Length: 285
Image: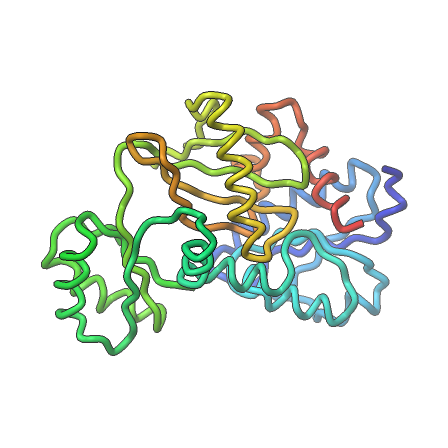
């Protein structure tokens, strides 16, 4: 790909979210890789510059290296769509739905994409009542995940429901999957990237058979695509003790630091950092 085909590129980085510092780190490295590949790239921090400057300064496309908040929830995607600026990763629906664990899991359940069973808790519920019904119906341990804390005993759940409804009007109480591990499949166009095991480090080889890895990647890519997400991201999943997968969530704005997942997945099969960034930007052509 001739670098001049990309035109003038903005690397979106920084922003106003809690994850600002990680985004600066991603962005600085994406910018450098693009510039090393000959691409006319420039940083653009939307916490500090007005979004209209993109059109006014002739930027034709953006590599989005923002994390969290408006960088990942469809807001900046919508605003860029409106200004005619192409960008990496998922459009408005994919991004909005991808950050919404509740609706992601409803879509999955209805389309047969396996995902851990769960109950919803809503700001204003009888917290003490629900806890009782939820532990009875689902078991322990549970995870309390605000839609947009691990709980191991029944009487600890109320306090966690009270606390988690402070962060979202909708709280997903999810059954924990035991005995298999946590994994992630990085998605970057048609690049064939290996499954990574996540140890709460990132572990390659993930320790599954090549056949299992191959079928889980197809399934992962489907879990991602059915939400409207396209081109670039991750799908996280648990395996139970027999190797049955359960998808947890997707990520539509993955880290691009030197210690982030996709660079580690890429390097493991001989794809350099620079090649990864160029290929992900290439999808916007």
